[PDB]
Image 1 (cartoon, helix red, strand yellow):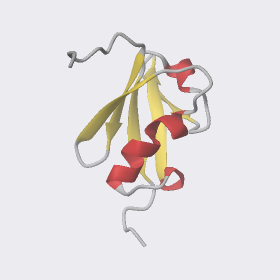
Image 2: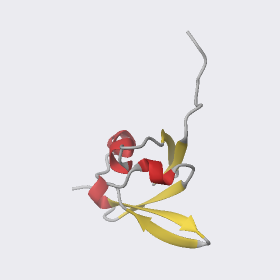
Image 3: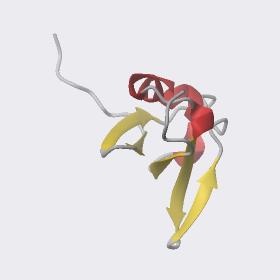
Image 4: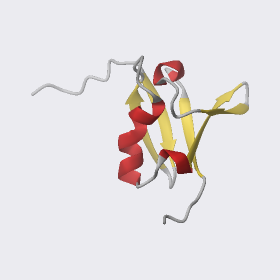
Length: 86
């Protein structure tokens, strides 16, 4: 056994209903494929969830299929497009 080793570059994603998670920013991997676990455990599909970052005080939208490496050290916030789960 060894202690935790988070010595990797990461991204801070805030999930709906006061939840949050941190994922390692890897080159080649998309934000979608990174947060797929977080979405799954929340029961949310990527197409019903919107992501944005804050730059110079402005909220700019982000595509799920963008490489998470582009967001190394960014704090993301998720929005629910349709709250009622069908």
